[PDB]
Amino acid sequence: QNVGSLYKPMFENIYQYTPPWSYQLQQNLNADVFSGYMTNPRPFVAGANNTTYNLVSGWNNFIWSVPYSNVMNNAKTIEEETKDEFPELFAVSQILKVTAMHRVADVFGPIVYTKFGESATTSEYDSQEEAYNAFFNDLEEAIQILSDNIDSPRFTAFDLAYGGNYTNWIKYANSLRLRLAIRISKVSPAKAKSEGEKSLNHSLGVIETNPDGFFVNGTLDHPVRTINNSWGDIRMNASMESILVGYEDPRVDSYFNASEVVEGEFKGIRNGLPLLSEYDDELAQKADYITFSLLSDEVLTPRVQLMTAAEVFFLKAEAALRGWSGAGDTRTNYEQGITTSFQQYGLSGISEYIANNTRTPIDYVDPVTPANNINALSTITIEWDEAASNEEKLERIITQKWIALFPEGQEAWSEYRRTGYPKIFPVISNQSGGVVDTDLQIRRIPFVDSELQTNPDGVADAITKLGGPDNAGTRLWWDVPGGNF
Image (cartoon, rainbow, N blue to C red):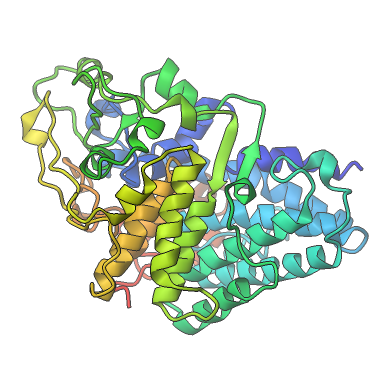
C-alpha cells in the first residue's frame, strides 16, 4: 500500500530522531530540562535562554513545527485515503496523531487539531479542552475499529512499534487514554473518571508487560546520543542526583554514568544556571560542567521510548487512589510499577527497594560552585504508606513514575506541572522579569513565531482561549491551582 509508507515519518517525528539539532529544539532544551531530568552544561546566550526563563522563540518554534510538518499532514492524508476504504490504517494513524499532538496541547494549551487543513490562509485553534475531547473521541473510534480488525496482519510491514499486532495497539490506546484521563483529573473529575474507566474496564485492558510498552524500534541513532556524547551539551540534572542517589536507586547506573568531576559518583547539574560571574564566557563555564554525569548508553539506543509499562501501573495507582473502578489496589499498582521498571533494565534488589522506608532524596551539592547547593526539597520515602495523606500518596506515586518515565521529559514535565511532584529544584537564575515564578516554575510556552507571522488571526483567537496572558507563566487548562484533589 502507498498509505503504508506514510507511517515512517509519523513514527520518527513524534520524538524526533534526526537531525539531532532539531530534536534539541523540539524537546531537549525545554521538557528534558524543565522536567528535572537533564541539564545543559553550557549557559547558552550568556545565560539568557529557555532554562533561565528568558525564552528563545527561535528554539521553541520547533516544538510546533516538527509535529505539524511531519505527523499532522500524514495523519490527514491517511484519514482522507483510508477512513472509509481501510479503517484499520486510519485507526493506527489516529493513535499516532494523538500521541504526537497531545504533547503539543500539553505545551501551548490551544492547538490546531479538529480544524487542521481547512484553509491555506488561516488556521483555527481548538481550546485545550476541545482538543482533549477530540483526543478522547479519536482514541475510542480507533480502539473500536482495531477491535473489529484485531486479527488483520496488513499493518505488519509498516509497524515500528508492535510488528503489526493490533492487540498491542489497542492496549496502548487504552493506556494513552488513561494518561490523558489522569491529566484532566483535576479540571474535569467526572469526564476523567468516565474516560479512565473506559480504559480500565476494556476487555483487553492496558499495557501490563514490558514488551507491550510503546517504543519506536528505529534504525537511526538516538538523537540524544549526539547531544550527550558528541556535543557534551546535556548532562545529568541535580534533581535526578538527589532522588536517585538518595534512594540508592540501581536505575542510576542504567540512566547515567559515574561522573568525572566526582570519581565513582553520579553528579547532576542544577538547571537554570546563569553565566556565573566566576566565568568570563559560557565556554569557560561549560568546561567545568561537561565533567558531570553523562547519560548512559542503555537509554540511548535506536529504540525510542514513548510509554513504558511501568508508567501504566503508576497511572492505575493514581486511578485507584481517585476511586476509578477497575483500577485495582493502589499499593499493588505502585509496587508493580517499580518492579516493572526494574525489569525493563534487568535490575535486581526490587524487594529491598520496595520495603525501604529510611532512604530519602539527598541534599544536592555542586563541587564546582558551592553557591548552587540546595537541601533536598523532596522528603518522601519509597515504601507505600497507606496512612499517608492523599497528597503524600500522590507524591509517592508521581515521584516513582517520574523515575520510570526517564528519559522522556515531556510526559514528566506535564506531570510535574499538573501535580507539583516530584519536588524538583527551582532554577538558580530566573531571567523572566517576573513573568514566570521561580518556585511554581514554568507553566507553558507561548504561541510560536511562525504562527504570529503566518496565522495572526488564529493566534489572536487562540489567545482568547487561554486562562491568562499568552506567556510562559500562564497555567494550561488542565493545570488548576490548589490541591490535587
